[PDB]
Length: 195
Image: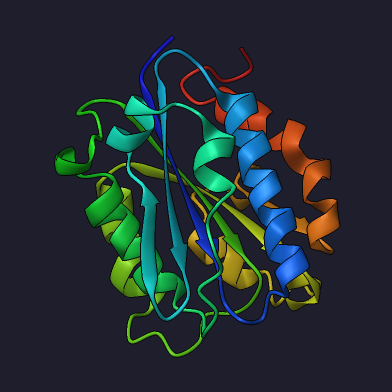
């Protein structure tokens, strides 16, 4: 029963086909409904080689209905600037001007379908700031892009430590639903280890 500001950063690159993008929206909608608590607020940013704040924590507070907010979003297409996406989440979504609560838990769930590409920023330019700001990061790597162990190193770089408790890997978008319970349990364990 502690305030939690949970942000989602979703990859909208052209590497994701339309049907899969819709599967991702369903996943986000469902997870938000399952994480829904009286003192929890959600915010969502989509990213590619453009960035779009679909809803701020303030907007969610005024209309706390995940599905209604997520369902209508359209895919940006383009490349994959994951690092800049993380910077914008930290500076924009978790900003008081957008409804973030001072002293609340700061949680970020990143959903990516591929390796960072075309980004002027490297993870070394954005992760330290995210850590200093206290943003707990979870990452979901979808598809063959992260089938390998070596490829998952990027996921480990994005997620908070230890990776074993913050990194999720699914073979495709249809399998996203298979980690919904696991993701909820981990986020619910924040500030309450072992419960």
